[PDB]
Amino acid sequence: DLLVPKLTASVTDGAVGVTVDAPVSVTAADGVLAAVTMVNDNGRPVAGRLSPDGLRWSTTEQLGYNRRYTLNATALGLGGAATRQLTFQTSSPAHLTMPYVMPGDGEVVGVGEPVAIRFDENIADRGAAEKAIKITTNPPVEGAFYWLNNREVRWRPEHFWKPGTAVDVAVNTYGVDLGEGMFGEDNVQTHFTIGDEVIATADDNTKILTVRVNGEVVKSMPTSMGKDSTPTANGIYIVGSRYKHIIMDSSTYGVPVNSPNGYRTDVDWATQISYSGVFVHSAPWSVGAQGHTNTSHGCLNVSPSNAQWFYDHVKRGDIVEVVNTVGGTLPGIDGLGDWNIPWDQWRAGNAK
Ligand SMILES: *[C@@H]1CC(=O)N(c2ccccc2)C1=O
């Protein structure tokens, strides 16, 4: 004869510590769903949708933390009715943390821009954070996570992006335990595209900064780099913020302004290429040295003409490579020196 309806929920009655990273759902068997309601302690209805066939019902909005939810469902069929009531307690985070993703949604960036996810708290379970971040690419390319510090994680392929590539980032950290009770405050989703290949190279042996667009030299800039005592580091740099004019306070980098190697002046047409202070800026006071000798604290001294041209034609994510200098190699965890870490080490990751 007719069979008694059966109900199924994605939560268990009496569950404590239920994660809010997924929807709560009720499914019916041997019948249809006649009524479903979910409420918090205070009694406010939690939004939900029922499938046209009446078999599946799921929550249509996020669920809060430290909540006591009550789910009431009724199934009807030819073989009778069934009513269930459930109550579960959602997660109680010891602390929350909001993610911050760059580059911004819709941007077009150079072939060296890595996907960056920054949290405003230290992350204790890095693997949980890597698992909660989805990275889609078209054309699909291999990539890998690597942490610069306890709070920011990066993702890039082995070699520079092939132009025209779409990148989609889905940081689905809400409802996910990130260690020691650290849960996500919200989710984020950005998308960006890779633009022209723009690789600029600065050779200390020639003291010249050459900008190449799509493999073709388009500009040759005489420059003066870091002097022997405060030299520019060799390696690959990624282009960051661009300023029509920027006040260079030495204290920003921990070096006191009232010091031999300190400084507090205002320069024009500055393109940041290092968190540690390396720039490409306008330096009128060194035109004579530019192209011959080094007389700076680390940034590439360029004429106002060329500096502005650099400002106008170089976008976030383009590459600046420095070679044959007397200084060392840019640290891989600088924040813009990601490509200076060997691919094997980067791929391996440091999730611990
Ligand atoms: C790199 C960092 C900075 O701000 N620099 C500087 C510009 C003008 C005068 C003194 C120092 C650099 O060389």
Image (spheres, grey):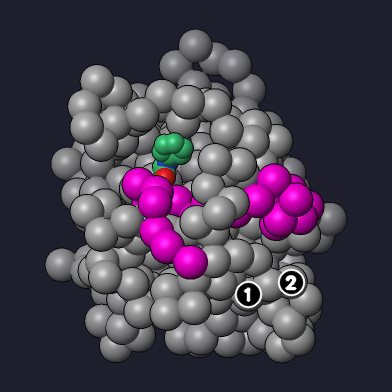
Numbered circle sitting on residue 210? 1
Q: Would residue 140 be visible to someone looking at this image?
A: yes
Crowd band around label 2 with a 10 angstrom C-alpha radius: few (<14), some (14–19), many (20+): some
Residue under the point 26% across and 66% down? 327
Given the image, on which type of amino acid does mark 1 rest?
Thr
Residue 154 counted in the magenta span: no
Which corner quadrant holds the N terminus?
bottom right
Which corner quadrant holds the C terminus?
bottom left
User: Given the current orientation, which residue lies at the most extreme front position?
Assistant: 288
**Does mark 1 have its CB less than 8 Å from ligand 1?**
no
**Does mark 2 have its CB less than 8 Å from ligand 1?**
no
Above or below, 133 relative to 63: below
Residue, disc 2 = 219
Crowd band around label 1 with a 10 angstrom C-alpha radius: few (<14), some (14–19), many (20+): many
Above or below, 263 relative to 306: above
Residue under the point 41% across and 24% down? 264
User: Which element is circle 1 on?
Assistant: strand
Above or below, 146 relative to 25: below
Left of 104 or right of it: where is 279? left
State the extent of the magenta-drawn residues as a range.
292-312
Given the image, on which type of amino acid does mark 2 rest?
Lys
Going from N to C along the chain, the mark reached first, 2 or 1, is 1
Between 35 and 213, the one nearer to me in the picture: 213
Task: Tell whether label 1 touches label 2 (CB within 8 Å).
Answer: yes
Residue 176 in percent (x, y) is at 37, 48
Residue 298 counted in the magenta span: yes
